[PDB]
Amino acid sequence: VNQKEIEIAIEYFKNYISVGEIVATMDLKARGISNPQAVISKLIEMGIIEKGEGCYNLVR
Ligand SMILES: [Gd]
Ligand SMILES: [Gd]
Image (cartoon, rainbow, N blue to C red; front, side, top):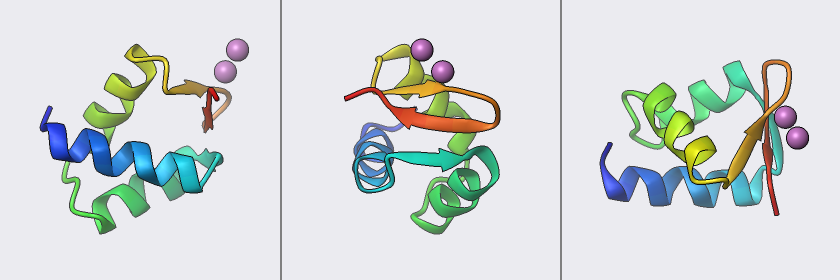
């Protein structure tokens, strides 16, 4: 997973606190992330975001 892509996704979830799986996937691809699934998994691993039911929440 690319480091610039990690920084792009982090900034995205900071501005969008709770976002659905499908909107997040669409919006991350729009900001140049071809594989948002991989970046999202890494952000969960890092404790940046948590996964609910088809929704991602910024841990804070
Ligand atoms: Gd939780
Ligand atoms: Gd959760």
